[PDB]
Amino acid sequence: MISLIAALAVDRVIGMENAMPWNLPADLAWFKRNTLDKPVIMGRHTWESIGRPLPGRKNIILSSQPGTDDRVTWVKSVDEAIAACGDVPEIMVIGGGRVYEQFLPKAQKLYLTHIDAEVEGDTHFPDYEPDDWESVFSEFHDADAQNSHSYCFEILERR
Ligand SMILES: NC(=O)c1ccc[n+]([C@@H]2O[C@H](COP(=O)([O-])OP(=O)(O)OC[C@H]3O[C@@H](n4cnc5c(N)ncnc54)[C@H](OP(=O)(O)O)[C@@H]3O)[C@@H](O)[C@H]2O)c1
Ligand SMILES: Nc1nc(=O)c2nc(CNc3ccc(C(=O)N[C@@H](CCC(=O)O)C(=O)O)cc3)cnc2[nH]1
Ligand SMILES: [Mn+2]
């Protein structure tokens, strides 16, 4: 099974200048809980944005060019990325925009954080058809001293 996980600001913005402007520790905690001990697939720009391997996960990087770091696994196509995960129950696709677009048609599950923040961005989450998805989990949180915006965790499953 292929799942996507992403944090979206208003208007589906997911990044600006290869970074995420906001800081929401609760959402990073949610990201770690849902990806730990699973393979994670990311594009090369997102790999450069994170800046180091994510521990406790098999890190698979998509790039058309040869790899430059043997702490992670480099692949050159979507089919190769899936094959490199082996026979696991759940593959996590962690972005960015171009990678989300390619894996959305294959995905059975979306883990989305909706952040109540208005951010100028240059990268967006794909425009997905709402009729294809059932919301199976929703959890809203007001802002607090550690998290400067309200946010909603949502899990969607393909109908
Ligand atoms: N809010 C969130 O949840 C979230 C999550 C992830 C990322 N982001 C943000 O997203 C932005 C980056 O997204 P992005 O769309 O610019 O880049 P990206 O999707 O992370 O990476 C694109 C690169 O990945 C390679 N690639 C993608 N598909 C490939 C394929 N089929 N075969 C071979 N290589 C492939 C290519 O690398 P080469 O050019 O080397 O060939 C391509 O240039 C950043 O701002 C990041 O902070 C946000
Ligand atoms: N919901 C969600 N939120 C995000 O911030 C997010 N970010 C990415 C890509 N960017 C990043 C950037 C940093 C870390 C990171 O440092 N994560 C640590 C958290 C450690 C902690 O919480 O202190 C990790 O171990 O997962 C992960 C992904 C992909 N999907 C996401 N999905
Ligand atoms: Mn806000």
Image (tube, helix red, strand yellow):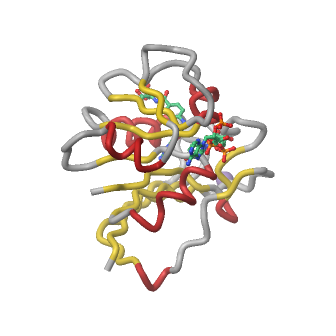
- The answer to which of 140 and 89 lies nearer the viewer is 89
Left or right, residue 77 beside residue 21:
left
The percent position of residue 108, horizontal first and vertical second, equals: 33, 65
Q: Residue at coordinates 40% horizontally, 64% vertically from top-left?
A: 106
**Quadrant of the rendering where the C terminus is positioned:** bottom left
Position of residue 3 measured from the top left corner of the image (x, y, whole percent):
36, 55
| x 61%, y 36%: residue | 64
Percent coordinates x, y for residue 146 in the rendering: 52, 34
The N terminus sits in image quarter: bottom left
Return the residue nearer the eye: 51 or 121. 51
In the rendered image, the vertical position of residue 122 relative to residue 129, given as above or below: above
Residue drawn at 52 percent across, 43 percent down: 144
Q: Residue furthest bottom?
A: 131
Nearest the camera: 35 or 11?
35
27 to 138, vertically: above or below: above
Closer-to-camera residue (101/49): 101
Q: Residue at x 32, y 28 (%)?
A: 57
Rendered view: 41 above or below 142: above
Question: Could you tell whether 134 is left or right of 64 in the image?
Answer: left
Give x and y (percent) for residue 114: 53, 59
